[PDB]
Each structure stands twice: as C-alpha cells, then as structure tokens.
Image (cartoon, rainbow over all chains, first blue to last red; front, side, top):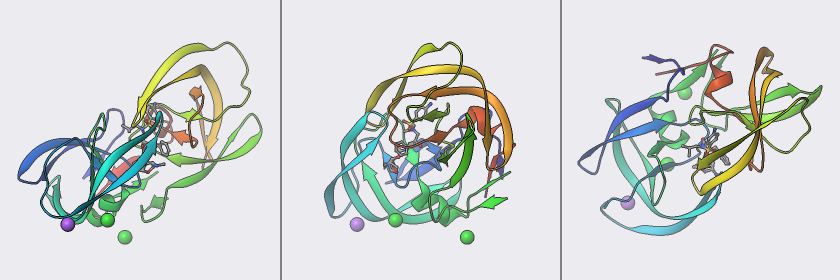
Length: 99
Length: 99
Ligand SMILES: CN[C@H]1CO[C@@H]2OC[C@H](OC(=O)N[C@@H](Cc3ccccc3)[C@H](O)CN(CC(C)C)S(=O)(=O)c3ccc(N)cc3)[C@@H]21
Ligand SMILES: [Cl-]
Ligand SMILES: [Cl-]
Ligand code: NA
C-alpha cells in the first residue's frame, strides 16, 4: 500500500498474541512498545528521544505482524507514550519513503 | 527518490541560507530543528516525545528546502537531539510511505 502523511501513519500490529495500534516511524531506529509481557530472555537498555531517556527491556527475535506482513527482530518494551515500529522492522516489510 | 530504511533517512536541508542535515521522520507531526536564528515572531509550543516534553519556539511560514524540494511552513526550534522533518513538511514535498 501507499500511505500518505496527512495523518499519523497508524497501523494494526499483532505481537505476543495481542492486537495493538502502532505508528510507522522512520525517525526511530528501534521498535518500542508499551509495557507488555514477551517470552524469553531480555536485557535492560536506555533509549533516548526528544525529552531524554527511558529505560526499556530489550527482547530479541520477536515475531510481529505489521499490517499483515510478518517480520522478526528486536522489540524494546517500556514506558513509551506511543507504540512505534522503527526501521529495524520497517526494512523487513520492504517499507520505503518515496517523493 | 525511493529511500530505503537500512540506514537513517538523512537528507540535506537549507534554511536561512545554511545547509544542515535532518532526519525524514514519519513519526513526527511537526518539524523541529536545533537552536538557530529565524526571522519574525514566534509562538510557544510544547512537544512530547519518548522521554517527555520540551519547550520549543514555533516559527510560521519559514522557507526551507528539503532534499532539493521547496517548502514553506512551520518550523519548531528547540533542544531536539537531531534535526527532524515531520509530516507538516513531508506532505509539502509529496512524501509517502510504501510497502
Ligand atoms: C536517538 N535514539 C532515537 C532514535 O532511534 C531510537 O529509536 C527510538 C527512538 O527514536 C525516536 O524517539 N525517534 C523520534 C525522532 C528522534 C528524536 C530524538 C533523536 C533521534 C530521533 C520520533 O521519530 C519522533 N518523536 C515522536 C514519536 C516518539 C511518537 S519525537 O518525540 O522526536 C517528536 C518530533 C517532532 C514532533 N513534532 C513531536 C515529537 C530512539
Ligand atoms: Cl532487529
Ligand atoms: Cl530493500
Ligand atoms: Na528472545
């Protein structure tokens, strides 16, 4: 699909058995989701944005379905105000910016 | 052009006759750039991101070139960690997300 940017590019994701709304965010290196449980090992990480840093849990090799396209990669979990799909998973679904 | 997301989507912008690097950011509603002087009056705004909120100066109707495409619109100036081109000017340059 082609998504225009008049409005926030929100899509439905499926992660950890749950449906969530998330923002397709080319300015995010990493995918960051609101607090939830995920299986397997994790390690702590700090990630910074506008406003400073938050502490997150880093889970590797997590499968997500993004607008119907499956991808696997690292997912950061913590107190983000918005669920964000970052470049680490946008590449896997073949997303590009075009102008 | 078609920009893939394996690396950060950085482009050259020109504002006040100066070249700067900035990130094409579909997760940003608004364009915000690091401290610089812009002409005219400004109005207050708060923008929130991953770590919380910052105060910025809002300048309207600023001429800015983005990857060679001319735009004229609102630029926020404040302590952002990186220059970000958000959806208000991405729509002016005709950008879409595609997958
Ligand atoms: C530096 N780590 C960063 C980079 O990679 C990592 O992945 C996740 C984080 O990325 C980010 O937070 N990306 C943001 C851009 C941004 C901000 C600061 C620095 C770089 C990029 C976002 O793309 C845009 N942000 C709203 C998101 C969180 C809903 S906003 O806070 O900046 C914003 C920018 C304008 C406006 N008008 C309002 C908010 C880590
Ligand atoms: Cl990854
Ligand atoms: Cl590719
Ligand atoms: Na894992």
